[PDB]
Length: 264
Length: 75
Length: 133
Image (cartoon, rainbow over all chains, first blue to last red):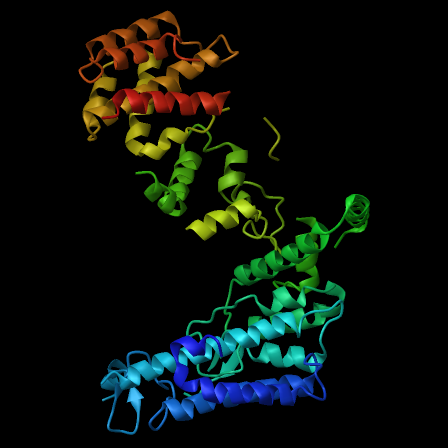
């Protein structure tokens, strides 16, 4: 709202309505860490969007199905469409580009809100969220677009996707706010989904380094708050682990990566 | 006059490190190969049964501090 | 298999393999005491005369001055090497200035402004300032 109040004021109105509706969708079960309210917020957001879209557009602001992404610098055809000239030229007036900019702005800010919520209200406890919430959040990193899966930043929307897969680490940094013992299953599921035919092909050393850096950071985060005696207890426990530690072809489970980060 | 070099470090330092590793003075030094090259080329005991057992996994990882964050903020 | 047995890094290599050529050239030159292939190496360097003087000073420090720091009396630059390189500096056309030639003849004879990294950085700064324009 405040952002849109400066860059695209024409949509303030709509927004200030949905705000209350948000207040109204979380009025009985505000445990957004659950399935019901989480899906409710996602729907409310897609509707605030999708209607900023229906109102900003003359007929439709759908991204370019051939660029497989946002139709930036598009040209408005007489074919009830807007497309980048290059693509459907190979296939063979700033109202629309200002509108595309405005919609991109609205979408960016809605995604900012979604991630800030998921990080501050959905991941904020000494306990984790439920299973369905994590599964939905993970599935939000993948899209079977019309033509082929694709990776997108954490967002309920399906219009902004990463053409060349980019395996970011945002859900992991959150899941690791808690003890690895609980979230290990979800991390392994994410690693399987990624290592799957979906995006990664071979020599997954970088994805493993990614998980490893994430776990190392989580552990440093948990140990930074340790006091003196807590620090010496951590030292003694690490010594015990090293004393008791000892040893899946061409495949690294998350437990192996955690042991790696720990010994590192 | 200085800042451009500070900006181009990320590409000028690897060249210097390669030249240092290749100089005959320490080219055959095992510690030099370790610090700069992959020790699998001269250490046979290195287990090579996994993807975790790679030098890149066991490469040094710069620690994050407030000063690095300040440098990033400035850049 | 690592701890079973020694050179040292030469950070000045940042100046390019031209510096490496001039370096090993003056090195063998001192090792042989018939220094004129050093003159051919100087001829080979395409950089300006100031940069050539900086390279000369850095190489002399890397191959001669450092050797004096050695607890090994075996490789201390022996007198013949000193007189050879001193003659060369006296006849050099790019070290003809008084301060640069003085600093070079100091490097050859371990009479320079005197840790290893700090010494290396200080000598580099001295060369840069003497030859810098």
